[PDB]
Each structure stands twice: as C-alpha cells, then as structure tokens.
Image 1 (spheres, rainbow over the protein chains, first blue to last red):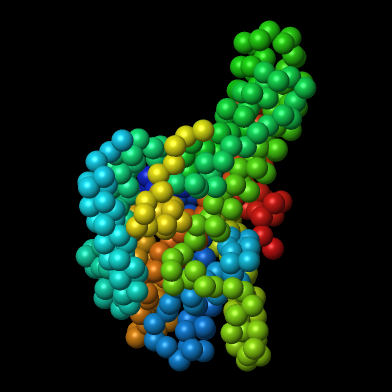
Image 2: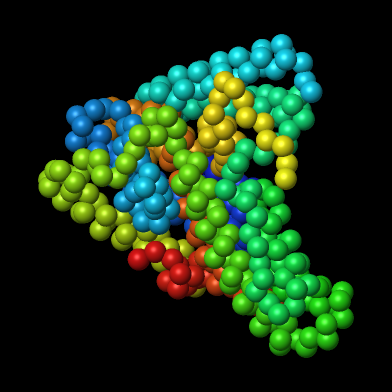
Length: 83
Length: 205
Length: 98
C-alpha cells in the first residue's frame, strides 16, 4: 500500500530543515511534495515577472535587477527592500 | 594582538576573494551552465565559504568575536508576564544565536512551566497555558520581524545596491505595467492552486 | 559587549551577505537545476546572472520558511502534533498572503 515517490531534486533533509527553521519540528509525508510544489510555483511567478522585465529591456539575460523588480511584486517576502 | 604583516596579507587575500566573487556574480549562465556542477554559481558559493573561513581566522588573529553585525544578533527583550522568572526564561528561549532560533508553542509552554516549577510560583495549569499562548504570540511577532529585517538589509549584492523602487521601469510604461498586473493575477491563482492541491490530497488520502 | 573585527579591505555589509549565503538550506546544484527546469519552459535562449540565481534562492527560502512560521504560530496544542497540508493552508488563510 504505502509507496515512495522518486525525486531528482530537493531532498527530504533540506525540507525538514526549512520547516524546523520555521519552528515546525515535525512534518507529514505530503509536506515534502507540497514544499517542492510551492517552491516551483513561487519561482515561476518571480521568473515570469523577471523575464517580462528582461524582454522590456530587450535583453536575453535575466539580471539580478530584473529579479529584484519581480520580487518586489510578489508580496511580503521582499517588502520594504531598498526603501 | 596579532602579527601586523600577517593581518595585512590575509586582508589582501580577503579582498582578492571579494573581487573574484564579484566577477562570478556577473557571469551570465545559459541553460546548459545551469545543469553544471562546476557552474559559476557553485564556484561563487564555494568561494563565499572559503572567504567566511578566512574571515573567521582573521577574527582569531585579532581576538575579536565572530559577529558580523547581523540584525538577528540583536537581542529581543521580553517583559510580557507578571513573573520576571518566566520573562527571563522566555528572553533566553528567543535569543539563542543562529538562523534556526524559532520556538514552537510547546517550547514556550515548556519554558513557562519550567520557570514556574523551578521557582515554585504555584501557578495552575490553565494560567500556565494562557501565559504561554500570550508569550508565544508576542515572541512570534518579534522573531518574524527580526528575520524580515535581517533579510532586507542583507539582500543581493553590488549589482542591486543601487536599487530604489521609484526607478521601476513599470512606473513609466503602461504596457509593461499592464502585463505585470496580468502576471500578478496569474501568480496569485497559481499559489492558491498549489496550496489547495496538497490540502485536497491530504483529504483524499 | 563583544569586540568587533572590521577588515580594512572589505566592508562588513558584504561579509554579512556572504555569511547568509552559507546559511542557505537547499543544496545549490538542485536549486540551479530547478531554475533551469522552469526557465526552459519560457525561452530556450534565456540566461541568468549568477547573482540573479542567488537572489532567487535567498528570497525563495525566506518565502518557504515564512509559510512554516505562519503555520507554527497558528498551531496551539498541549501535545505536539505533526504538521500537515491542511495546517499550512489554514494558517495561510489566517495570517498569510491574499
């Protein structure tokens, strides 16, 4: 019945550690998969905005500055940065 | 006091590591480079570790502490209860050094019960529980704030150090702003969708 | 108070940032590959400044940790429990974003 998913990617130890860094000592099995998913979605959101900026500048290279502009639009995470 | 000549040499080396880190930071990685264990990103990470070790050794040489002036180093006081024993124990709990200091409710409650029992304060169980919940809330706010500030005051690099929000290109370009708005509506939906996905999975199991 | 070392050749702000980068919990090769996995879907010709990957990782780890902080803060029980997806979601609806 029980089954182990295959993953090439973020390993369980790092996920348990991010959770712990949040004060969460114990996490379910589905939390690993969720954390990978949510991480992917967040990165997609940021990169989508960053590339919008990169294309507006007519570059092919996403810069750190593109990433900052994008990150500031993602809500609380970078809120307040730079002023 | 450390050898002046050796401090000078180590500081020149430190500056060299910094120059190379700045060089690596500006490297543009294509998609195949992002698949590479020897990429400039990983070279840069390893060089940062090397640098931090050297900084540590220079701190040995000058008999200084290892402190860098991080926001998370600054102590968070807690006076929140009417029992200073409890208050001290809570200050202790929340002021442990490191990126990982974030208690859960159980930790707070354990600190409260421990200070109680230790000092024989005669506090009953529901008073203890209420004290712990109020405390946990307080320290939660302070810890989250300290991390947020540590992040935003320590973010990025020389390439982003001139950032200011008033320079956002989107402010002067309505087409760009419109596309970003559209993106934002999509982003919010995608995040809700992944959160819901894993909740649903938890239920169906 | 402690004694503070302030190098002549490098500012402390720089040092703080390098230190923080060593504090990241996600292995950096898997991380850059996740970025590549995503970027592949957008444009075949995209490149990234290394510093942009760094900004992405720092922000992303902060984002995940804050999800857990919120969950932790909303979880009040006498006996410690294991954190589940529904807990993440409910905490997010209570103290989280949008």
